[PDB]
Length: 112
Length: 114
Image (cartoon, rainbow over all chains, first blue to last red; front, top):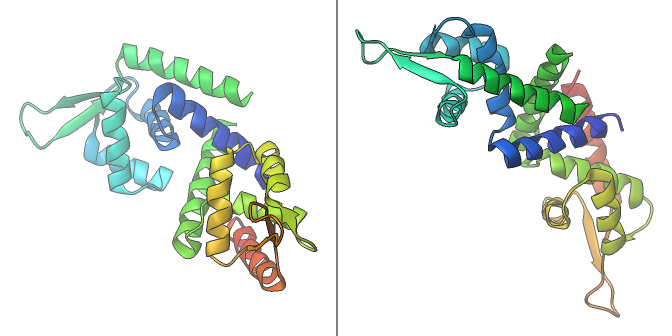
């Protein structure tokens, strides 16, 4: 009877975020983690994937889907190596950070 | 705070995967089945009287609820009986095998989260 409380608000958040932003709660968790890794500088993709797999317990393919979606929705940025084509970095620019803050202020208020 | 909700996101997603793999049930199905235990453990309940209750208690659409109820019945975790007089009228109920399945399932949930 204490689990249902959690379930209602979780389901409620998931629908709200989906409707308003077309993001899943996986995308949010991934985006949250990007803030801890590439706020000030860029980070290599293959690296971020291992960190994220361990910390979020998501498959590599679920992570790639989320990262690609965040980039597509202009909430995360990507830069390739001029040296090695197969090497990709992700990073948050200033627009991305301002979007991030707006999004999570919106998250906190929906929950509170 | 945010470590506790990201924390809870992990356990939540972990539970959903486990239940889906092992039972082919969603967490919606679980919430609905939990609610059935509070309404039709000892007697049957009219489908209408249940959909409204559940809609209010679980904040789910009538259609999401019909999907779950139908799935629970197909998975032999919930039972259904029709009126003989009005074909339109349907009841749901938990029989003794259903209750036994219910207990096994929730014991499994409770231990997975601990």
